[PDB]
Image (cartoon, rainbow, N blue to C red):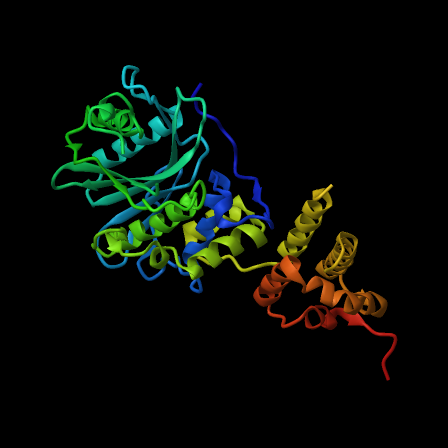
Length: 380
């Protein structure tokens, strides 16, 4: 069963305070990362390379116009239905692509048949073996380059990752055959043809990238957009970047983890940021939801400061910040309780959560964030 599935955009990507790059990616987290693209402080800022398009409408995709050349760049929102299943056994057919993914290939084909400018289509998706019951959802990146003069559609799959030539004809290891077939049928009736399909594979050293391969996919989305906007080649590890470390740097990783762990973003806010090219500033309500999530998670494990001390300090601070979110105003006793909890709130992982939101809200400390709202008892 690989059919269309429809979920709407009234949803929220919550703070996942326990997440790290090695914990894996899904379509929801990857979409949440798109908020980084117009934050000037981010290593993934795209604002020097592209600006927003109008529209030029491709359903399910955000349109950008290169600032340095004529290229239009279309980045598809991630979707759990973007799945290609391949059969490992070469005596079976090649596999399948989910109907929704197949519909997008037809929609890209219809767009290109009317296009007068060069365009680049960027689509994150997962490939997976379907007749071997261990099912790993391997995150990959499809890019399609359309050249109106050629007239060629050129697909490429970027793949953050030893059987003989004979067994490579008995066993498939990727979805290239079914994917090629699906693109081919989508364009059969057009006046253009397929360029050379290529799989650029780039992390052969293995550090159990089950994994951060979603983080490399997001990093490659940024390279494809910038490289396409600048008319340059897409440089990736082993082919432009000599180390994976200079490709996905510590700055890149911090940006990814901060966004996923600590932010609380509505889908509608991310669509607003990408269709108008704004940054999404951190709101105090995200601090609250981040602490709530932290407490909810801690209550489950595993059944310094004790678990009871940390949940006590988190309950106290959540109440104070809700008491600041409206009307509002906090008492001197609440503030005095909070002073006694500060050391506990700044300790270990709770402290990094607190420090991220302090920094992004404009306060140097828990006290300086709430002191403007304190009524003392009393004045002079």
